[PDB]
Image (spheres, rainbow, N blue to C red):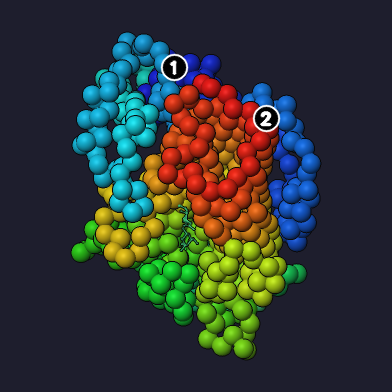
Amino acid sequence: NQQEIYAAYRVANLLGVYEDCSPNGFYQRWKQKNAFMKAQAEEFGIGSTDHFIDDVERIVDQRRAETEWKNADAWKNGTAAFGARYLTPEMYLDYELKSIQLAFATYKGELVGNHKCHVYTEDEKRAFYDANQDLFTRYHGDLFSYEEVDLIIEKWLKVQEYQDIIESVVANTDNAVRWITEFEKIWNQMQEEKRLRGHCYYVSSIHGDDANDGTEDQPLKSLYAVNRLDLQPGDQVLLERGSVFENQFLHLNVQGTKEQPIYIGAYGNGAKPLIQTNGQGIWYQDYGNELDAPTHVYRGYVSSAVLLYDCEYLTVENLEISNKGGVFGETYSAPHKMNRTGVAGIAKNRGTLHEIHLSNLYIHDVEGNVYDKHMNNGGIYFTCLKPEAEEKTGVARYENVSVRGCHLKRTSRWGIAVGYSYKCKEFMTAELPDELFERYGHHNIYIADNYVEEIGGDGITVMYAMKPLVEYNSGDSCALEMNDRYYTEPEDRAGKVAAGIWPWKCKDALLTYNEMRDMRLNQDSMAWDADSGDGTLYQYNYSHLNEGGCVMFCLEEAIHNEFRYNVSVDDLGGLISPSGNPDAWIHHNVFYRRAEVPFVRPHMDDGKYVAEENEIHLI
Ligand SMILES: CC(=O)N[C@@H]1[C@@H](O[C@@H]2O[C@H](CO)[C@H](O)[C@H](O)[C@H]2O)[C@H](O)[C@@H](CO)O[C@H]1O
Ligand code: NA
């Protein structure tokens, strides 16, 4: 809503968040941001996947072997390059609107223009605690103490005060109309620049006909027609910009070759083609065996806007996807609400699937089951099901798979999840020998340049992969539903926790050049999580105002952990959560903490760690 955008930049000006809070000011900051990331970030993983995807494990080995803080000076004076290397207009606007809100939350001034900044008294914060007990329970139902959530409550109350100022300015509607008229022109200009950045099948919801041959002159009309095409190596399917595919879905079982991949994309002019699945695109998921915990749901119907079922040598690019529920009989937090995906990837009957790539997808309002962790449930979820006959087709798993440039907003439960496998019970040791990955695990997994925001559960998680590279991702405001207010009927599933960007049962994972802000309080709610897995390294990551702190080392199977050359600015709760972990080497980081935010997070402090040569500032 343009009046809310206008109001936000009015507050930004009064807070001094940005020097120029005109629409041109927004445009120049966007241009500056993209030019900076292009000049200063690493080049690896930019451009065609054929030029780098085979080198992911090699670049991971090189970066893990670094012996000093690369560009330490930039990192320490606040001009390092991290987060997504290109921000779309939609990513950038949402990022700045969140920046303004968080600046209000930490503002110490008396006034914002004529608005007197409320000073939240102990009485007022304690009253909020007593009235919102459903927000302060942990994994096992035990409450955080008031003292543990005092500063988080003040942050929340200042965010509400901020939000009330926006609707107030909106209510009070001259130069607002000027500001908004100019913003629309700038927005269109930005969309024009964004847009600038076998057989060809054309599909047009507006001009097509499913009886056509599917040329640009006589395009197909519907995704159902696409679902019926016998797509061959080299084929392209191009969806017309401006198209809306109402209640439609793409369910594909197609294979290109290395030499002639299949491409799904956009053509023409206007908005990204919109797949508006609205809870249709039904299919039956079955892992074929219980998962790592017997309580995890592992079979049932899923709604997916885009289902890639045993696909290979396929790239999907430049689409907008939603998957809203709200069908008759359904409530939002219902225990068995259908699992929903924006893009679901499945490996089952073709052994290793090669060369699946998602690029520049805008996936929002995917209203999956609030609870279920391992059904294909969230914005993007790739999994591996037990093959019909593994002795004939091989272990179902992934090789050379990338998720790049995707924007996720309001997806539940997961943001981006890649790799959960029916072979999960083969990895139930602390140490994970390389042979487990040679037989059962994924190779050359690359997740980069994504923006995940307002996510029900975890932001980005890579699973069962050898040396995955998760880099140059930006995350805001994940774990929104990991609390009793939304997580109403978990039954025996537990799982009321989420962290930002992290690996599960990976070997020698590298998470680097990521940015994570404003994780929503739960027992976890830290930015980074060296979870169960072997050899995880976080380096060159930026974290800010996460309500569960900076980094966790999670229990006895989180082994060979290292956390170096990271910057943490005003993480809350407690900076490090060494929770029952056997080791963690925490060294050569820079932390900025409030005096009343401890280095070690309460109740998550009984693990083994070496913290040395860290620079801890008070703020
Ligand atoms: C060991 C542990 O408790 N780790 C937590 C994570 O929970 C595990 O996540 C994996 C995901 O593949 C399985 O679901 C497993 O059964 C869970 O125990 C949890 O997701 C993260 C993020 O909050 O943190 C740990 O608490
Ligand atoms: Na294969």
The image quadrant of residue 399 is bottom right
Q: Residue 524, relative to residue 199: is it above or below?
A: above
Note whether ligand 1 is within 8 Å of mark 2.
no
Of residues 233 and 346, the one nearer the viewer is 346
Of residues 170 and 567, the one nearer the viewer is 567
Q: Residue 97, relative to residue 605: is it above or below?
A: above
Mark 1 highlights which residue? 15
The amino acid beneath tag 2 is: Trp
Of residues 264 and 139, the one nearer the viewer is 139
User: Is residue 127 visible from the viewing direction of this image?
Assistant: yes
Q: What crowding class fits label 2: few (fewer than 14 Cα within 10 Å), some (14-19), or many (20 or more)?
A: many
Please, what secondary structure does the residue beneath circle 2 have? Answer: helix
Query: Residue 94: percent from the left, percent from the top?
Result: 46, 36
Q: Residue 270, relative to residue 442: is it above or below?
A: above
Tell me which residue sits at (34%, 27%) in the image: 154
Mark 2 highlights which residue? 75
- Looking at the image, in which quadrant does ligand 2 appear? bottom right
Tell me which residue sits at (64%, 32%) in the image: 614
* Picture disc at residue 339: none
Tell me which residue sits at (40%, 25%) in the image: 105
Indicate left or right for 132 with 608 as reference.
left
